[PDB]
Each structure stands twice: as C-alpha cells, then as structure tokens.
Length: 121
Ligand code: NA
Image (cartoon, rainbow, N blue to C red; front, top):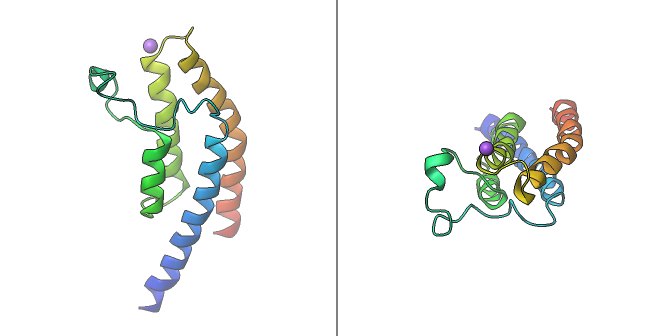
C-alpha cells in the first residue's frame, strides 16, 4: 500500500533527524567515555549493577535499523547512558562528572529536537 510507503518516508525522515541529534549529543563526549558498551571482560560484575546498559554505538545500531519509533524512545536510551553512569560511578569520578556535563549540554539539543519533531510532524 501507498499508506505504508508514506509512513516509511516519515520513519526514514525521523531516522534522518535522529541521526543528526545523535551526532550532536556525541560531540559533547569528546573523551568518548560513552562511545562503546562497558566491557564485561573489564567490569565482569557490571550487570549485577546495571540492568539495561546503553552507549552511543548501541544507539547508532538501533537507529540505522530504523528501530526508534519516536523521539521519546531515543531520549530514554540517552537517559540510560547518563543514569547508568551516575549510579555505577561515585560522584568524585571523571566518569560521573562526564555524565553530568553530557546531561546539561545535551538538554539544549533535545529541547530543539522536540520542537523540530512536533513542527515537522
Ligand atoms: Na552510586
């Protein structure tokens, strides 16, 4: 049907907007602390602490599989990156401090992407 194609043109457009958003969020992690999953060879107990790990490459794979159905799902994954890090690491660590900075700086980007997703439909 033509109705499923017009849908898929929009999902494709949403994928295109979210790709831009992701690149801007990741530019706020120049240390690349959140780039890749936490290593289970290096932190073997990690899953005892964190039930839903998340990182930027894992979000990218989902994105390129058009697996985000809306901005809310994308944001949830971004928040997991931050919240996991803030639980697993103590307050006086470079890791915790990096997540605080990413949250604060990411807010500006997510605020404008909310408006662009509503505006464009
Ligand atoms: Na903690």
